[PDB]
Every structure is written in C-alpha cells, then in structure tokens.
Image (cartoon, chains in turn cyan, blue, yellow):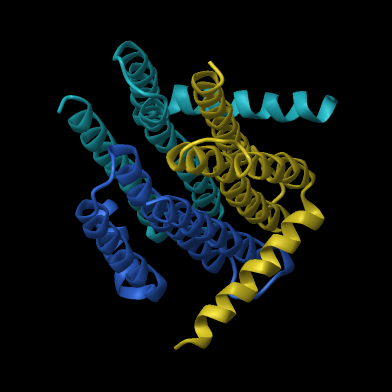
Length: 115
Length: 104
Length: 116
C-alpha cells in the first residue's frame, strides 16, 4: 500500500503548492466549496447536484494541469534562454473553456430549477 | 493568453476547427431538442471536454517541439500519450450522446 | 484528408498501449474504470445518471493520460538537465487526485439518491 501513500503525498504537495503560489487556484477552491454548499442547500435532484459540483471541479483539474505545463516551460526557459508562450497560451485557453463550460452548466441548470 | 491560444489553435490545428464546429453544432442541437437541463448540460459538456483536452494536448505538443528539434523516445511517448487522452474524450463524448439520444 | 484521422488514431492507440505497459497507476485505475463502466451499464438508472457515472470515471483516465504525458516531458528534460524539483509532476498528481475525488463524490451522490 506504500505506493498509494507516496502518490497521495505527491498530490498533497502539489495541491498545497498550487494553493500557496496560485491566486486563481485559491479562487477556484473557494468556488468549489461554494458550489458544493449551494448545490446541497438548494432542493435539487442528484444529477444536477453532481453536475453543479463536477463542472466546477473540472476547472480545478484543468488549472492544475495547466500549472504543471507552466512549470515545465519555466524550467526550460530557465535553462534555455529562449521564450515563446505558445504552450502557456494553449493551456490558458483550455482553462477558459473549462470556465465557460461551468458557467453554461450553472446557467442552464439553475435556470431550469427556478423555472 | 486565452484568445491568443484559441486563435492559434484554430488557425493551426484542423482537428480543433472540426471540434469547434462540433461544439457550436452541439450547442444548437442541444438547445433544439426537448430535453431536461441535465441532458442539455451533458450534451454540451461532453463536446466541450474534447476541445479542452485537445487544447492541453496541443500545449504538450508545443513544449515537446520546443525542447529539442531531434526526436526522442520520451518526447514521442509524450505526444502519443496526449493523443491517447484526446481519443478517450471523444469516445466519452460519443458514449454520452448515444446513451442520451437513444433514451430519447 | 480522411487518412489524417486514422493516423491520429494510430498515434492514440500507440499512446494507450504505451501508458498501459509503462504506467502501473494507469493499469489499476483502468481496472476500476472498466469495472465502473460495466456496472453503470447494468444499473437500472436513467440516461443522465448512467452518463454521469461513466464519464466521471473516464475523466480519471483522461487526466491520468495527460499527467503521464507531462511526466514524460519532465523525464525528457531530466536527461539533459541535472536538477528536478518535480513540482510539475506533483501538480499532475494533484490533478489526478481531484479527478478521482470527483468520481467518488459523483458515485456517492448518485447511488445514495438511487438506492436511498
């Protein structure tokens, strides 16, 4: 079972790292907990609760992966002395799409619920 | 950053153009059918996910290309891995639409 | 070009096979994924519930694949360069963790409403 505790350790190291270093990530965590609270407090069916939570967590996932990519790029540029933000742009685009997905999700779901 | 990368992906990646077309089409079609909110959301999200994953994969490909002009086993592995991730997102999207529309 | 699709699919399967052979976590999570997918196709639930149960778990697959790609990039860099903070690897590990947590939460909320 050791590999599991090692991996989870790496995961918490990463999460704490992202929380301390990235402001947008802190905002996204706030967004997740708020999402759960709102979804559970509102009298809402299971699929919709799930969707309201998942759509927001997806943002966190994509943000983390993006941050990983940014880190790789930064190591490169540190040793490379050449910079092109192609990758960073693409990642940020991905995160944007995730956010738009969450807003659409919440719009449709909450609009239906309060109809 | 954002619109820069999106414009980049549209101009360069063909699969991304096809995915954008697929996304907007999916939006229209999801809004046309008389389905519930959860269904609509799933129909849209499933397609948007493909776009997201394709974008991340494209970022990875960019990094790999920047690292070295020469091809290496690990660099190739990375690309292949990213291509695999995109594949799964598509299958999921397909499965999503199938379960939903068959039920409808 | 219609052939482009089959080329990209070839790359894709090459990557799936690569991930399965080299990455163990991908194998185990793959077992849990396939199990979950099978179970979802036999549960007496609505389309939305089934799609949710399946997709939530396939997300784990996708994120693990991306994490593996990133790890491959870091491993590539580590041959040329000597020091590695492994911060990127940690971030990816975090992403996978969040994906899994999402899957579990999804299954709990869904099945506790279903069976409950």
